Image (cartoon, coloured by chain):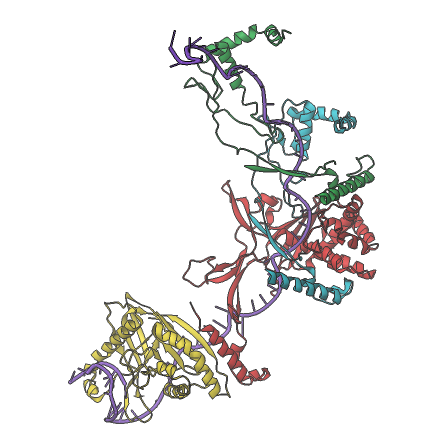
Chain colours: A green, B red, C yellow, D cyan, E purple
RNA sequence: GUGAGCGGCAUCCAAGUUACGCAUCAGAUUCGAGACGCGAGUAUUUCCCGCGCGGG
């Protein structure tokens, strides 16, 4: 679907001296701004280098309510890594998929998480007996995790 | 600035809905084909969400008076009864374009497309009239939010509220009114009746012969003929309405202008039915920000004296120059 | 199933036969095709057709009435009214002739209820050899409902309207008697009965006719405006 | 629903000598206006600047429908939540979108849900659960100076 | 026994941030549910349409 977006020049919506009272200079500043805007618009119309605040464009989005499939493969992981991925999936819905921060785009909800052909998703989240080992392993790894590994990984030989 | 006006119409209101609708002879709207089907001019309706007592919300058609009609009624009242006499007292004349802009918001169908200077914007928005409505070549935002006329009905309670629940009506408030048209010549039966007609009997017989000639075609236009039996739908008389006017931060002169218009509002019909005296209403209460400023003599009392003083002062110094500047095209 | 009725308001109430003669004289001037079509005359001759005449006449409170049975007769009346109205306007410049057109729907249906109908004028005799069969009411009554049923079937077939196959029409009584005179020069007055009432097992719609010699306008009756019993 | 809007020509409705008494040129100007309108209409119809007469339609959502507005904030301070709740207290004073002339967009807030908790009272957003937000935003406003806005708006080049 | 035979382009990386479809506009002007179904014309046969009988 296509969504149309507009931007307005705030100084053009002033209609009383009260609205321009907060503006330093006030009516004189507003008149100067509007005169410059009119001159720039006339120059651009004739030529057909600053740009004004009036904008009308569109962006194209995927409609809301469509179901997506996300496939994650891991090359022979330890139980700590599987548990970490499961924790991220449990806390993933709080995040947002792509851009569109201002318009609250990218919000989603996880419906089913399938782990090697079996469903491990509950109303609470990724849970069950089959995932206990992964969660215990990742909890132990987190308890034993320190900045030393990151520091060694990020260090440059030269 | 909230204004709520309680209006009771002493004649039916006829705001015709665009489109061609047909009614049978028994009142069946859009009757099945085969029976007699006469054209019906429906009354304006707006579908609104309402509760019928079962606790669920459904969209139901509510007969209203369109808000643009009421806004133009207010504008015409203000002009014809307050501002036109004020300009005539000073012997000030508005140009043809300025008159068009004052009476319809613009003089031509092509907008200027460019903004107005801030000084011009504040000058017009401070004006008692042009500030309320706005428009013009370089489109200006008016201070007036004129809403539609909502009948006090069980269907509008989800909109107007329950403050006026004592004036509500549960049933329907519309009625089919049947109109006709008999041919003048078809009523002539004696030679002395047509003594005024050029040729009298000869002319009448020629005209009815032409009518018969154009009537011979039934099935397989120009000169339909003076004969008709149609109907129109009117909101029945006596129903109490609510009119809501909201004004965006007005000066006392503009409020006084609105109050003067409300004082002289009952002198103009609401909508339609001029030939049949439709649209006659009386204002029953005017509420200004939750307070009732209506008296049997109109809008009076010390609560509104400052508004009247301000509008009188503004009118006593009102010239055509503001209207001429407002209607002037910058292209 | 349409029967076109046209009313002419001459201003003075008109006789049926006198109106027929007057219009025939008036039509004689205008295009002969419409003339022979109007009075059911074969083109080039002046003979009354064997088939059920579809265009006939009739009286009115202030003039004469045109009754065009069937779709064809209705169409003939519809495209013949302007010319006859113009002729009437020419003939009487001292009065304003006014025309209103009433197009009726013709239908007949059967009901178990017995419906009573009244006919103002009835004619039941054409020839003395036929009057030999009319010498008494004993043979007259059978002739009566026979004539009614025959006329109903004839008009139904002429207009192409199916009729209840289980009809039983019964004559009820009489009130008055009159005389039927075909031509001004003819000395013979045919049989005429006034205030005739009969019972029929059907709801009659539109306008029906009974009697003899449809081309004058006697023996007519409107079932629509007569209501029922 | 569809609302049908019409624009009239004032001069066509002008049909009395007193009505044209306010116009410069009097009846001559109105006659010129009407005849020019007639000429333009005839030229446009024959052909197969725009006049004042119009007949349009605009489509609106009916009155009385309920709406859900979802506002999400990532890791806000107390002052920012207080500012949002203050805006929601005075939000009904402004219209949603479009139709300023015809008073469109008016609404009333039925409920405000604050992370699963309803904080809407008949007199606005009130309660002990919202007291700290209002206090924080009040303090922030009392300490609000234009230097932040000026620094924000100043270009770096 | 093909200048043959043998040989991983592979690993790692956010298209994101900000933006009012808005301002202005009479569904108006004209016209009747009120008119329309016969008490209209003599005595016994005349030219003819289908063929004793139906029928101008």
Q: Can residue A17 be seen? A: no
Compared across the picture, whether B119 is left or right of D34 comes to right
D130, D123: nearer the viewer: D130
Compared across the picture, whether C84 is left or right of B147 comes to left
Residue A115 in percent (x, y) is at 44, 17
Residue C7 in percent (x, y) is at 43, 79
How many labels were placed on the picture?
Answer: 0
Location of residue C35 with respect to B258 vertically, above or below: below
Residue B233 in percent (x, y) is at 54, 59
Q: Can residue A70 be seen? A: yes
- Residue at image position (50%, 12%) is A81
Location of residue A82 with respect to A2 vertically, above or below: above
Q: Quadrant of the N terminus of chain B?
A: top right
Location of residue D35 with respect to D81 vertically, above or below: below
Residue D154 in percent (x, y) is at 77, 28
- Residue at image position (40%, 85%) is C27
Q: Which image quadrant for residue C104?
A: bottom left
Compared across the picture, whether A20 is left or right of E30 comes to right
């Amino acid at each position: 679907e296509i969504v149309w977006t507009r931007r307005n020049d705030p100084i053009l919506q002033l209609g009383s001296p009260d609205d321009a009272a907060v503006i330093e200079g006030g009516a004189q500043a507003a008149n100067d701004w509007i005169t410059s805007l009119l001159a720039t618009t006339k120059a651009k119309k004739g030529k057909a280098n600053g740009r004004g605040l009036k904008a009308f464009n569109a962006h194209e989005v995927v409609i809301a309510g469509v179901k997506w499939l996300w496939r994650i493969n891991v090359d022979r992981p330890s139980e700590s890594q599987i548990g970490l991925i499961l924790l991220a999936l449990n806390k993933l819905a709080n995040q947002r998929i792509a851009g569109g921060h201002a318009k609250d785009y990218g919000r989603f909800v996880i419906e089913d998480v399938i782990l090697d052909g079996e469903s491990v998703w509950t109303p609470s989240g990724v849970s069950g007996q089959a995932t206990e080992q992964f969660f215990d392993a990742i909890a132990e790894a987190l308890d034993g995790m320190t900045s030393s590994e990151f520091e060694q990984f990020a260090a440059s030989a030269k | 600035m909230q204004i709520e006006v309680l209006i009771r119409n002493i004649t039916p209101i006829f705001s015709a809905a665009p489109g061609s609708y047909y009614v049978s002879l028994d009142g069946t709207i859009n009757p099945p084909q085969g029976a007699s089907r006469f054209p019906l001019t429906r009354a304006r309706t707006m579908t609104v969400v309402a509760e019928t007592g079962d606790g669920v919300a459904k969209a139901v058609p509510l007969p209203i008076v369109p808000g643009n009609t009421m806004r133009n009624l207010l504008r015409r009242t203000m002009l014809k009864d307050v501002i036109e006499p004020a300009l005539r007292d000073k012997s000030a004349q508005l140009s043809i374009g300025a008159y068009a802009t004052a009476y319809a918001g613009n003089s031509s169908g092509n907008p200027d497309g460019v903004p107005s200077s801030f000084d011009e914007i504040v000058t017009m928005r401070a004006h008692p009239f042009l500030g309320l409505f706005g428009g013009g070549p370089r489109m200006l935002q008016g201070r007036l939010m004129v809403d539609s006329l909502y009948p006090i009905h069980q269907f509008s309670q989800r909109i107007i509220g329950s403050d006026y629940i004592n004036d509500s009506i549960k049933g329907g408030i519309t009625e089919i009114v049947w109109t006709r048209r008999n041919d003048p010549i078809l009523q002539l039966g004696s030679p002395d009746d047509a003594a005024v007609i050029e040729g009298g009997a000869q002319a009448a017989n020629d005209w009815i012969t032409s009518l018969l000639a154009t009537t011979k075609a039934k099935k397989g236009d120009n000169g339909r003929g003076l004969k008709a039996f149609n109907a129109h739908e009117v909101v029945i008389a006596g129903v109490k309405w609510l009119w809501r006017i909201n004004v965006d931060r007005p000066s006392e002169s503009q409020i006084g202008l609105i109050l003067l218009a409300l004082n002289k509002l009952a002198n103009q019909r609401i909508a339609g039915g001029h030939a049949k005296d439709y649209g006659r209403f009386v204002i029953e209460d005017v509420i200004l920000d939750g307070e009732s400023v209506w008296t049997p003599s109109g809008v009076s009392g010390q609560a509104t004296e400052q508004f009247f003083d301000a509008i009188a002062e503004a009118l006593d110094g009102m010239t055509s120059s503001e209207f001429e500047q407002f209607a002037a095209s910058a292209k | 199933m349409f029967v076109t009725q046209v009313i002419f308001n001459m201003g003075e109430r008109a006789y049926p036969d006198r109106a027929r003669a007057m219009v025939a004289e008036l039509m004689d001037g205008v295009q002969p095709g419409l003339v022979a079509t109007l009075m059911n005359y074969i083109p080039g001759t002046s003979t009354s057709r064997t088939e059920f005449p579809t265009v006939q006449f009739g009286g009115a409170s202030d003039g004469f009435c045109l009754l065009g049975f069937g779709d064809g007769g209705g169409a003939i009346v519809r495209d013949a009214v302007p010319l006859i109205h113009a002729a009437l306007a020419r003939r009487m410049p001292d009065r304003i002739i006014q025309v209103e057109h009433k197009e009726h729907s013709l239908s007949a249906e059967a009901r178990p209820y017995v419906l009573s109908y009244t006919v103002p004028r009835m004619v039941v005799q054409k020839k003395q050899r036929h009057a030999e069969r009319l010498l008494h009411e004993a043979e007259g009554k059978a002739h009566l409902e026979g004539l009614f049923l025959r006329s109903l079937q004839r008009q139904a077939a002429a207009v192409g309207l199916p009729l209840p196959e289980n009809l039983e029409v019964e004559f009820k009584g009489a009130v008055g008697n009159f005389a039927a005179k075909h031509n001004p020069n003819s000395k013979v007055a045919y049989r005429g009965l006034r205030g005739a009432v009969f019972d029929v097992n059907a709801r009659l719609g539109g306008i029906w006719t009974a009697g003899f010699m449809l081309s004058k306008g006697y023996g007519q009756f409107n079932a629509t405006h007569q209501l029922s019993g």
